[PDB]
Length: 117
Length: 105
Length: 91
Length: 112
Image (cartoon, rainbow over the protein chains, first blue to last red):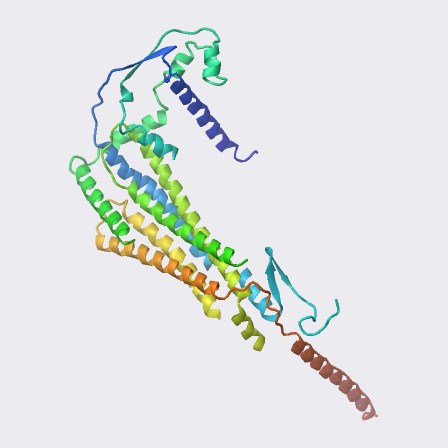
């Protein structure tokens, strides 16, 4: 598994941290070993950063989006300009059928009169 | 699913989690069966290394630098274009969705 | 038989069409920019970038599936087309 | 006959065209200066018309196949006439060989 081990690192590390998250929540369902107590608090805004940054979600990640859409589009536009062509000439001279999932033809003079089995 | 489910089960119709005072009772310097069956084979001896590991809040520094560049991108032209662009993009976004959804009848 | 294969083609076509349309509608669903509340701005920003990335990937996959369907239709018609076969035979 | 193939490949073209134009729209709706809103409506209409005519063509093609499908191997063929023509070609070849041989014996008699 020498390839995809780096993704494996990032995911097992994210796995251990979210295991620590299920751990803190496992102590959050707890009233033994630890008590809950609610009192609120405040956090003044610096800006209207949800919107502002969301617009960057469009800039940044819709640029990644549009990039990948245009990248698929350039790959395909290149790709279109060979199997299915050859099948035409073959089907034009010889005799073919499809049974199961493969493609099978005949050689025998059998539709033309012979009975040689 | 996991993202959208947890996100809507948090930010609507809830008692507020950002209240809770977090105050454990004791330190358990020893291996309790409470831990091993409460947590399914984890949680070593609860101690002064895992008190902060539990109650850590400072994130990694890369997002801190990101927040520094958030201050930077807020240092550009603002207080006249933030709300203005929210208005414009909101309106034309809504118009777009209206038009595309409208014609499937 | 042959009815099952053709109805499978119909199912694949309608599934992929509704999938791409639904994906674009959800892209415009998350496209409304609003004010935040208890959502921890950077987190949903990063994961919405992630969601639009995976949705663009879904769009590309939908296009590739349509290409595969077109190729399969091309194979099917040439092999079982009685009228086309006859013209070649008479020439 | 061939028209069917031509229309199918044209449909391929329109598939990639729809992807391209959608990418174009989402280029426009990230830039701050989205001024060409008439042309944004243009690109939305391109999205719309493209998707419908693609789905239209494929649905029509499926119906046509639903009227031409029978599930049998179609046992016509064209082998006999091809044997006959091959026979005739090798008969002509025989003739060409014998003619060359006569030619050389006459050639050698004329020369003393």
